[PDB]
Image (cartoon, rainbow over all chains, first blue to last red; front, side, top):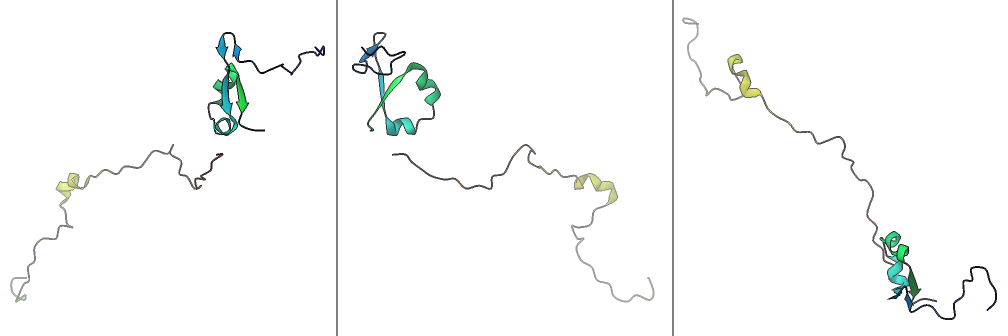
Length: 50
Length: 50
């Protein structure tokens, strides 16, 4: 609506992308992850934090 | 030796002595660990991110 180039805002965070639900990881779990390089390839949603 | 010596003392042959013909009984093996090994001088720190 605002005519932004590569807008970082969404009306609501997608429930599904390409027919599959987006992975959700809590911040505490994400902080301790040692296989983060594989995880960020697909994309995820960080929650359980402010 | 036969005339002037009066009394003689005998003991069992010490195991230290070895004849020269039996030199191969002195061959022994020692193992030194590989030089690629590195020995650690630093402690291990325990932590968690909850």
